Length: 49
Length: 49
Image 1 (cartoon, rainbow over the protein chains, first blue to last red):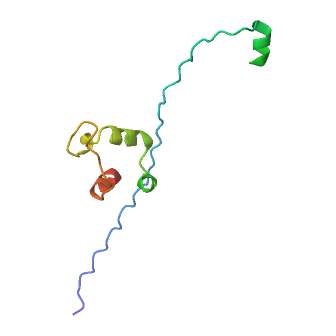
Image 2: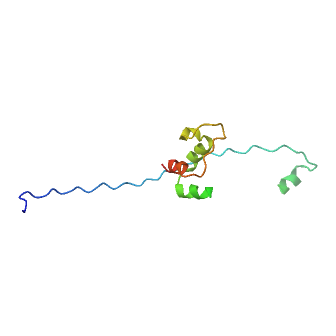
Image 3: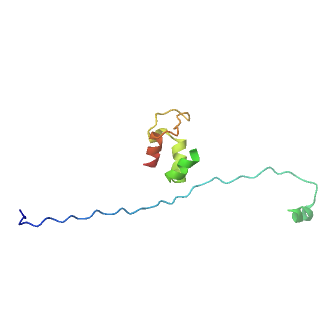
């Protein structure tokens, strides 16, 4: 009962290549607040800022 | 709870914005900004896919 033919040999499966996706988002920029005038002249307000 | 599916799903941020902003295009029945996906499992597996 030993077969004369030799058995066929299986081919192993292909492994999966794990891949990541890196995307970026776009947040909208902020606008300016309102111009509020003050009492001070230029150099004092400049140094303060 | 709802942050945990965001952690475990691994979806990127832009498609997540797309999913919340337009749930109907991902196959939920449509209703304008009222058609809400729950935290049920059929609307987990489709995000995962």
